[PDB]
Image (cartoon, rainbow, N blue to C red; front, top):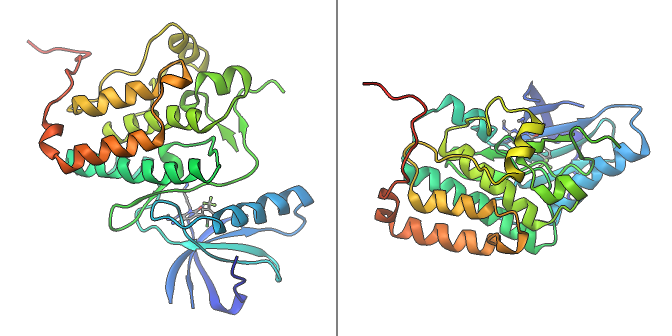
Length: 273
Ligand SMILES: CNc1ncc2cc(-c3cc(C(F)(F)F)ccc3Cl)c(=O)n(CCCCN)c2n1
């Protein structure tokens, strides 16, 4: 990792220790701080995140500019993504993109995830809230925090309803549980940030999934896209596509965009006579 001198960094606005938007000697950056009195574990997790990010060089993975580790407070400095987190972005831009644009976002995320998987990195917390969007509509995987627990664990919280059954039931997180999560992200994108499973409780979601229920088709969703997210949600990991398969399929759909005009039937929850 590049060590950056503090005189080269100006913090400006809190966008999230805190996360600031700032300027780096000038390019816009995001800046994550570690406050005084941090523990050894905090330091290893914090610098650990920078270490992992520094190992990656891919269009669809947030780029590390560098770290401040020789001076306090310590900082991680990344590229700045002008449109912020994908979940909030979709919800504030409801209906404003083409289906081709939405599918192109998902291709970008899948390409990032394929790279992570092949670099032997399991994300464990893939969700639209952990994807960032730039002014070219490029989606990039973010959140490489080391210290993550599944929420509601008897023994950062990973939410149940984005997580694959095997990861919940016996703590088996793999690139195949990340594919499950990616299927949920597909549904988030195609619904402009609808909350998966609505007001169902965690227990209700888990029971539904184990009984074979799956999220219904988004409105105006290409048949091929719904089929692909459904395959991501196979109970049996071996029947899920790999990210390599997902990228291949999305690339084919984008290159033959009339393929996306065939829509999955939408089951209307209310009909009007
Ligand atoms: C709004 N635009 C914007 N642009 C770029 C970033 C980069 C980071 C980031 C990510 C990592 C790592 F590792 F997780 F990828 C590390 C360090 C940083 Cl600074 C970040 O935390 N935020 C804030 C997200 C708030 C959304 N809940 C960003 N926000």
